[PDB]
Image (cartoon, coloured by chain):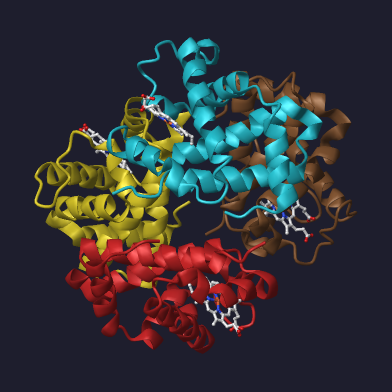
Chain colours: A yellow, B cyan, C brown, D red
């Protein structure tokens, strides 16, 4: 579970991302499509090239859920229940892929937040996301 | 991958009793049941509601047969596997959009179908050999994803 | 969450295992040291020889914990002279090996219980041991 | 694993500005902090509870340098990785008994330290070349495990 200090480091780090959140979104994705080619098997309908507006718009939506998530850190299973049903039932996206996004997302934060991304914050951030990933796979079976 | 001669013959000999039509079908159907999300490819098949109609669907059986068959070819190419399924790794990728975890998934339920088929004969040394096959085979089939 | 049709499946499966529990635990273990050679990195102080009285003595404990889990299907940990939070802190076993033990402990049951190993009781057994690994890896960080 | 003429250049060129001593103890330290179960191979270093203590632990630092040191010398021979690491693979398995999944966790932490270090200079195409490489080194240290 996230310790109280974890919950503080996550909100402290996200607060600093700010208006750039949806910006970092598309970047975590591009890094994912490019680093782990396998991840783009779920996007036959998306122009995945760089510059792409679809890869940008989506990143904004990925940013929004982690913001709603940070907002409801003590109640993620209820605030992300909607998406969990969307990924497992309607998308059926294999659980080993979220571990893949969370890594690119984390690298993307190590690239823009060098002051804040200390070893302590890094760890709390690897937790927060693992907990998100978990919630998103709750409804697979 | 290289296989210890007797560990290579445990594969060779046991395969010859495998009813590829019963094990092929059960390998796929038991996969569509256990890891639910794997149906994102099998929607054309039809009725996959309860684990019942999943197992009894003549499409699931039908496709598990040609899935096991191709496996039953790399069993000869037990040296260079890549230069065999590399063709199917293009397909399953570019055209078919299949996530490689599902192959890794197949190999494990298959290991279980065989043990459900040979009970006692499926000793640990034999399972272990059959693991060296399935993992390596899974990676050959997912070698050049771009 | 294990559905109610799951609990009753898991229960009948293990009750059928009866006294054979320890017999089975030890078998899944040896299957694991053979199929997945990396798992041996955690038992370099165990007599890993065929027929070993240290693995059989270990398969017993593991089964005794799996029987206790089943017999308190609303709560998964705590058992023997040191579990409770034993793995997370003392052993520190990488979470990745828990899925390997569960696989091998399922092929064991698919081998000896071919009649109760319907492709529905297999899904419950799978969801069960996944819920146990999830509980044992619960307080890791 | 495979790489390409242009990817090698990005790897090699981004490795020149790397301070192996620094990043070595920066990566192993952040590994021991994000995945504290890896501390099972380090009772013989000292205080490893608080992150302050892990990072500035002179013994962590001394060993980070050794690892990344021997990591660095592996980039040179990027066409024969499994060979180059055959003797460290056998030493980690037999002698040290180091679960190979530690190498993958360390590779992921090493990529974050390299993004944390180069900022924008560590673009998406640099991460993808670096992921391939760190996955490459991990399969190479794990090859001699039995
Ligand atoms: C780490 C957790 C993730 C977050 C925060 C996230 C969030 C979301 C959100 C907010 C949507 C928008 C749904 C809508 O309104 O249409 C969505 C859609 C989707 N997600 Fe996830 N997701 C996550 C991980 C994944 C991963 C790893 C993949 C697969 C590589 C993925 C694949 C999809 C797909 C394919 C869509 C549908 C896009 C479309 O066709 O319009 N998600 N996700
Ligand atoms: C590792 C064993 C496998 C082998 C050797 C194999 C073999 C085949 C072959 C030969 C084709 C059919 C002919 C064609 O489309 O041109 C095919 C297609 C396909 N495979 Fe596989 N496959 C395997 C595993 C997978 C996995 C793990 C999945 C399951 C999620 C899967 C899902 C599909 C799908 C949906 C198609 C497209 C429909 C079609 O068959 O035409 N395959 N496979
Ligand atoms: C998910 C299934 C697991 C269960 C139910 C389980 C159960 C047990 C039990 C009951 C004990 C003995 C407690 C004591 O003696 O105080 C124990 C100890 C231990 N477990 Fe686990 N375990 C599991 C997974 C793991 C995994 C996956 C590994 C690594 C491959 C592992 C490695 C160990 C080791 C080394 C010991 C200590 C034995 C000794 O040296 O005394 N366990 N486990
Ligand atoms: C991918 C990079 C890795 C390389 C190239 C590597 C390299 C080395 C080297 C050269 C040594 C010296 C062995 C000797 O004295 O002959 C060593 C020792 C050791 N390694 Fe690894 N290693 C790597 C990853 C790891 C990881 C991931 C851990 C665990 C977090 C680790 C744990 C050990 C241990 C326990 C020792 C001895 C520690 C000491 O006495 O200072 N290594 N490693």
- In the drawing, does residue D34 fall left or right of residue D111? right
Work out whether residue C73 can be spotted: no
A129 in relation to A90, above or below:
below
- In the drawing, does residue B17 fall left or right of residue B104? right
C24 in relation to C92, above or below:
above
B25 in relation to D51, above or below:
above
Between A86 and A76, the residue placed more toward the observer is: A86
Q: Residue at x 42, y 37 (%)?
A: A137
Q: Residue at x 60, y 23 (%)?
A: B20
Which x, y percent locates residue B132? 61, 48
Residue situated furthest front in the rendering: B76
Quadrant of picture, ligand 1:
top left
All told, the count of numbered labels is 0
Q: Determine the image quadrant of residue B87.
A: top left
Q: Residue at x 10, y 47 (%)?
A: A52
Q: Determine the image quadrant of residue B43.
A: top left
- In the drawing, does residue A105 fall left or right of residue B104? left
Which x, y percent locates residue B88? 39, 37
Which x, y percent locates residue D130? 32, 67
Q: Residue at x 45, y 85 (%)?
A: D65
Which x, y percent locates residue C82? 76, 56
Q: Determine the image quadrant of residue B99.
A: top left
Between C120 and B47, the residue placed more toward the observer is: B47
Work out whether residue C111 can be spotted: yes
């Amino acid at each position: 579970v996230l310790s109280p200090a974890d919950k503080t480091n996550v909100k402290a780090a996200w607060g600093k991302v700010g208006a750039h959140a949806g910006e970092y979104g598309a970047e975590a994705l591009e890094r994912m499509f490019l680093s782990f080619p396998t991840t783009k098997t779920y996007f036959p309908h998306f122009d995945l090239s760089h510059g792409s507006a679809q890869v940008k718009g989506h990143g904004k939506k990925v940013a929004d859920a982690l913001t709603n998530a940070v907002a409801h850190v003590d109640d993620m299973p209820n605030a992300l229940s909607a998406l969990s049903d969307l990924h497992a039932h309607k998308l059926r996206v294999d659980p080993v892929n979220f571990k893949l996004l969370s890594h690119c997302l984390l690298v993307t934060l190590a690239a823009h937040l060098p002051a804040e991304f200390t070893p302590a914050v890094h760890a709390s951030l690897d937790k927060f996301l693992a907990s998100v990933s978990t919630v998103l796979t709750s409804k697979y079976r | 991958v290289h296989l210890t001669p007797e560990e290579k013959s445990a594969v060779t000999a046991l395969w010859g009793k495998v009813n590829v039509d019963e094990v092929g079908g059960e390998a796929l159907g038991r996969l569509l049941v256990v890891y639910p999300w794997t149906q994102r490819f099998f929607e054309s098949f039809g009725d996959l509601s309860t684990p019942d109609a999943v197992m009894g669907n003549p499409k699931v059986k039908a496709h598990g047969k040609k899935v096991l068959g191709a496996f039953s070819d790399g069993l000869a190419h037990l040296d260079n596997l890549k230069g065999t399924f590399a063709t199917l790794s293009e397909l399953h990728c570019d055209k078919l959009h299949v996530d490689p975890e599902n192959f890794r998934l197949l190999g494990n339920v298959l290991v279980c179908v065989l043990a459900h088929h040979f009970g006692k004969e499926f000793t640990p040394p034999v399972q272990a050999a059959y693991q060296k096959v399935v993992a390596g085979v899974a990676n050959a089939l997912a070698h050049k994803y771009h």
